[PDB]
Amino acid sequence: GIQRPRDKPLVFFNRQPSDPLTGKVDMAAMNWNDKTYYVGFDAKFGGSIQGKMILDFLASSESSVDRNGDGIIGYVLCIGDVGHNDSKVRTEGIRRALGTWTGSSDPGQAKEGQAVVGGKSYKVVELEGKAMTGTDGSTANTNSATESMGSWVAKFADKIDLVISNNDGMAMGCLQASNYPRGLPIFGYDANADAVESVGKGELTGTVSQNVDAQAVAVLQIIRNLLDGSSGEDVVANGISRPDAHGNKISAPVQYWEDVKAIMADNSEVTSANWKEYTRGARDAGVRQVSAPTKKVLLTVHNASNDFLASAYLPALKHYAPLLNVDLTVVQGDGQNELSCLDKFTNLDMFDAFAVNMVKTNSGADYTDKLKY
Ligand SMILES: [Ca+2]
């Protein structure tokens, strides 16, 4: 077993060590030891994946998708918080995919695009892209999306061939319109439980997942690999992109970015073809019970009140950990003060490895200071 704390595995996850202003990765933190890694997802490519989902849908569709037969695929777009990078990325992704991108992710900025539908070339028009703001100033507002959808049906009628949304909340809001045209294709983003259920019902046409289960498995699997004596390629491949010695393997695609020591889950489209893999509580059948020696991990969460971490990430971790014979202890902070986590990152001698979700992305050395000796 590893004798010195400074040599024990350290997996940063979900918030990447980096300068908070520039995003430059903190390689001092990443190079703590050669058993230090980061697990996240391919976030910058999320909009590309949403775009590709829509293009693939159109490519395998028939001309009946063109409801008014005018040779144009018309769409309406629900934009979330206009100042938020997620809105910008997703808007850019779908506009570039459809050829309507002009250089701007703003509402009202689009040009005529093009796409293949059922083996024929069509023009594409963004009939309207609009931020869904509540009358209280709230962003990505569900009720505003419902109202906008109803007004869009009234205004554009059967020029609307599909609805695209920066997120699931707004797409589900559109589906609440009393005049939602039956079967009209609609796409969201986030793979929320209700959205995936809707995909299963053939209502929402598709959404996009960050593969939280793959990320949770990767954190634990990296640690399993290291504590069992893997070093180098096997650490980031075994159980991750190919089966490990027990036959376990993450089902979703996962990347490794060597320069920053980051294991990054792909974003995945969620459609009628795979929706059951993404429903609330669904777990990866590719990860089964192992008989490896039991090991102890202390894992931190930067904010106990973060719903994604509380409701999606942590339950995934707790499902997979026992399967990998990891005894997982979890401590959780307040989302504001690093000390809320640091002061709980204690009695480290009880553990074999560590997983850290920092409040501030530049706090790496405060954690490694505790593992020096
Ligand atoms: Ca049309």
Image (cartoon, rainbow, N blue to C red):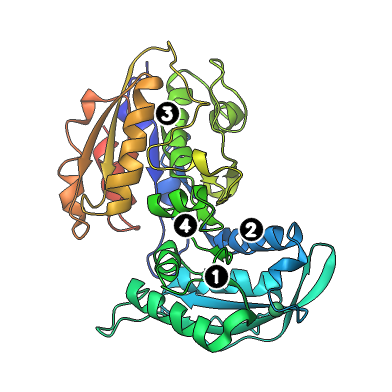
Asked whether 318 or 189 is in front, the reply is 189
Amino acid of disc 4? Val
**Mark 4 / mark 3, whichever is N-terminal:** 4
Q: Is residue 372 visible?
A: no
User: Circle 3 sits on which residue?
Assistant: 223
**Mark 1 / mark 2, whichever is N-terminal:** 2
Q: Which mark is residue 53?
A: 2
Cβ atoms at labels 1 and 2 below 8 Å apart: no
User: Circle 1 sits on which residue?
Assistant: 164
The yes-or-no answer for disc 4 within 8 Å of ligand 1 is: no
- The residue at the point 20 percent across, 45 percent down is 332
In the image, which is nearer the foreground, mark 3 or mark 1? 1
Q: Which mark is residue 308?
A: none
Amino acid of disc 2? Met
- Helix, strand or loop at mark 1: strand
**Mark 3 / mark 1, whichever is N-terminal:** 1
- Helix, strand or loop at mark 4: loop
Q: Quadrant of ligand 1?
A: bottom right
Cβ atoms at labels 4 and 3 below 8 Å apart: no
Q: Is residue 300 visible?
A: yes
User: Circle 4 sits on which residue?
Assistant: 25
Amino acid of disc 1? Ile
- Number of other residues with Cα within 10 Å of mark 2, as a class: few under 14, some 14 to 19, many 20 or more: many
Quarter of the figure with the C terminus: top left
Cβ atoms at labels 2 and 3 below 8 Å apart: no
Residue reaching furthest right? Answer: 120
Q: CA distance from mark 2 to mark 3?
A: 33 Å
- Helix, strand or loop at mark 2: helix
In the image, which is nearer the foreground, mark 1 or mark 4? 1
Task: State left or right for residue 55 relative to residue 212.
Answer: right
